[PDB]
Image (cartoon, coloured by chain):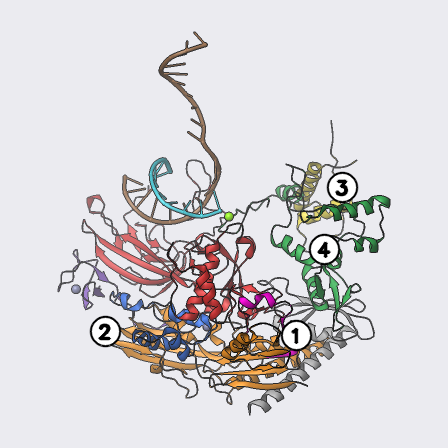
Chain colours: B yellow, C purple, D green, E blue, F orange, G red, H cyan, I brown
Amino acid sequence: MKIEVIKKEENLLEFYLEGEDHTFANLLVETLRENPHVKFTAYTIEHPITMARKPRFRVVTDGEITPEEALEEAAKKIFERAKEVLEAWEKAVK
Amino acid sequence: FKYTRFEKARIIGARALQISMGAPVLIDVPPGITPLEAAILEFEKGVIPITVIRP
Amino acid sequence: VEAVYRCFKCGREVKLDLSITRDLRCPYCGSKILYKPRPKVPRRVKAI
Amino acid sequence: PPYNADFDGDEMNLHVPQTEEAQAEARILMEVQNHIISPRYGGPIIGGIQDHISGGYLLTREGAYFTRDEVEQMLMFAGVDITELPEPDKYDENGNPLWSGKTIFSLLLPEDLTVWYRNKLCDEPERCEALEKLIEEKLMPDPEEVRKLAYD
Amino acid sequence: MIVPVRCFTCGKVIGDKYYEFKRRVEAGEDPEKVLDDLGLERYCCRRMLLSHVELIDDIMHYRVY
Amino acid sequence: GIEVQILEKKEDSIKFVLKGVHVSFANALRRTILGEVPTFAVDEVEFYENDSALFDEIIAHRLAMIPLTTPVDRFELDALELDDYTVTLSLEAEGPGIVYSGDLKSDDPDVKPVNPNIPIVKLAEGQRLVFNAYAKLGRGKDHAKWQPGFVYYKYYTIVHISKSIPEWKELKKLAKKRGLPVEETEEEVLVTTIKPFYIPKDFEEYEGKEIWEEIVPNTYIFTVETNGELPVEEIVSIALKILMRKADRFISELQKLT
Amino acid sequence: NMEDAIIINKASIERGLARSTFFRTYEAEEKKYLGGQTDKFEIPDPTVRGYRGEKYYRNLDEDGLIFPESKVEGKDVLVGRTSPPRFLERRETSVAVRPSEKGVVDKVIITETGDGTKLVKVTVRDLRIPELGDKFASRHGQKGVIGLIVPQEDMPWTESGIVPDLIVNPHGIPSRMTVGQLIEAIGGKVASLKGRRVDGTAFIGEPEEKLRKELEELGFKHTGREIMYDGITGKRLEADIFIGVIYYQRLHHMVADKIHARSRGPVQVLTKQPTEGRAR
RNA sequence: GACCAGGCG
DNA sequence: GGAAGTAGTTACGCCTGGTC
Ligand SMILES: [Mg+2]
Ligand SMILES: [Zn+2]
Ligand SMILES: [Zn+2]
């Protein structure tokens, strides 16, 4: 899932998440929002037809953690949450 | 001296037409720029060799 | 040239050549209309 | 509105200028950035039509508040460049910060603009007259005083 | 023409249920009860069985050869 | 923590409660179930002869819409890159009658139509329909033919009906009729909304303050249904593994960037 | 869906919603000119005047007619035909599909005219899956074109598990004053839930009050509004969304039959100006 | 090529 | 001044087919 950085200012990272759609982008931004060190995070699909699979992100942190750290921690939390839900589901179904 | 809309359009069109026939660009332009965009960049910078005459 | 042809009213096959035969008719029911049949060759179709 | 097109089967012709003079003429004199103001009446002809107006009302009306995620998403969707959200106006019963629609709308206005007027939503002229009386005294009313007498 | 294999809205397979629904309804049973028994709870699925026309029978008669 | 509680486990569907999870993860799970989990579906058909009334395109689409059993152990269904295994389903049918999905053969014992009673075409006297249909893995985000089933969720809400309300017993009886779990106290009656509880017209005057809904935070009632391609538990497990693998791929790409 | 545009579901289209096939029948006659100078159904040799590319005769049979069920694209010939020379070798007058039309050869028939010359009709069928620009209408006069095709996972859904097959902007309702469309949506939902079709006759049909009461008794809100969730973000919408079943019909004004573009081509002999028409 | 008819905005 | 005659116009495209 290719990352196409557009901006790398101080405490700001804007990039294209090539290959994804709303499904992963929304989860990533909502799990990034709960990080206290992130001041502004959002995403948008510039065009439903032309850029359907190229979401664009903006991650702005206060400065104590770089946006790359924020995205890494958010993805780790997503993976942990999915694993926990998988364990609960497999316990319940069996 | 303030150009009108029509004077600006004529100047930019003539400059783009000249550029398209080998007239050297008077500034530096990004690669891939179309001649019309080069003429518009020239006008926005302010280096305009063409002068309009008025009655 | 002998070509395989199918009649209109009846579905059973009729053989003739258009270039030579001035009159086209099924010689069994007298039908003037014929179908050019589907060649027995594979056809690849995308299911979408 | 300029084309009077309504997407019910409408068709439009597209002409490609071929000479550089024609291309310059089109791009300088006929672009859609210009012609926002109609030569007929000297007023805006290119503007919001139905959904822009209704969404603006749902945004800026009294009591309309938005959550942090909604505010960030709408700002990114609109294309507004921003690196920090303004201070929230209210706080939810759960402590969640909430932004007013007026603040979000103000985020995309020029920092020097200042104007007042009565729109079509004026049903009690007394409140409008009170606001005008407050404004006329000094022309720079205290923002909290206006917020006390704010009217839709 | 012929009964759709899947519900246009949610993709539930309703191809097999049409003939059972038709024969049960012709038998005089309540259509709501029949549709509930067949398992079609969402009204999108019930629309597919309730509004379908078997037009294949009326066009099978003309051959292209 | 995160709790999963199953309300109604049927053969072709399951209804469970998901607790302690944000709305974003619930929506992501629903979207991954709808468009990520891969199944087998006919993608290409080779027609040798088709004398039927339907055209080749129509029959090919109807074949693609026919659900196909998807083996689970043999193939990695949670992989981001799908396998290219192709199953050849053939049909040699002719004469008067109606062609069902159970008449299709298969080169693979595992991959075959789940329901053998789905009509394909009605054949008259003398008509022949011969084809070889090829199936391959895919995702519902590409075409609807690869959708494993249907999925949706809703908020887990408890409706409070004040017992000071006249003829509240009618509301209690309506809640019992809909099958919703209902509890009553000295001051009010609580109707857990497993299924949409809509207040009738007569009681709409109290919808503001006397009767009101309470959304339980981070709780959702899910409803997953299969088309026979996969077990519903397998569908949910594969979707969760898909989300895990997507997160892992994002982590790897992010580390590659730095 | 602004300005009378219509938003539609991709999954519904892929499952057969509003799918259609377009038929065109090309005709070629073996004309008998004066003096016994006839034309011939044949695959012309490249020595004939006006010969097209040898690729355009790919599907032709030695008889001179294209085999059925053979995929034919634009400018491919169906009836190879040569006419006696009239230039001032045999000229070519073969019949090919129209330049903007493709499809599959559904049927090739051969027959005899009234005067006795050979006549052939070739029918080409093109599959038209709905796309952006195709015109849709309801029985209440609400015309519109597909403004967007949205995946199912992006469509909103109802608490009952109902996903729309189509979304219409509310701004087209009040200016047009089509209360009948709303009543028809209510009636369609009630008919689907009951398993009995609703009588919508002009003046003796089922009253709207009866339909609303029946919808109330079936377990749904009497207004027809339902609690809906946003597909993109996952939270329920603030307002209760009006949803129902409306009978929409696809019109033959497809965007594939109307798109036209001419860089440079034939001109009229008299005025040297470009010709007139999409067909030429 | 011009005549007719039917539609579309 | 009649009181008739006469002439001159009556939106813009676009598409389809059918016959000469
Ligand atoms: Mg219009
Ligand atoms: Zn015969
Ligand atoms: Zn359904």
Alpha carbon separation for disc pair 2 and 3: 83 Å
Horizontal side, residue F226 vs residue G121: left or right: right
Q: Nearer the viewer, residue G220 or D7?
A: G220
Instruction: Report how far apart the C-alphas of labels 1 and 2 lie in the structure.
Output: 57 Å
The residue pinned by badge 4 equals B30
Chain under disc 2? F
- Residue F119 lies left or right of residue F87; in this view the side is left
Q: Name the residue under label 1.
A: A27
Q: How far is the residue under mark 4 from the one under mark 1?
A: 39 Å
Image mark for residue F126: 2
Disc 4 on helix, strand or loop?
Answer: loop
Do the residues bearing badges 1 and 3 touch, measured as CB atoms within 8 Å? no
Tell me the crowding category of disc 4: few under 14, some 14 to 19, or many 20 or more residues within 10 angstroms, Cα based.
few
Label 1 chain ID: A
- Horizontally, residue A21 falls left or right of residue F47, namely right
Can see residue G129?
no
Label 2 close to label 3 by CB (< 8 Å): no
**Residues drawn in magenta:** F197-220
Which label lies toward us, 1 or 2? 1
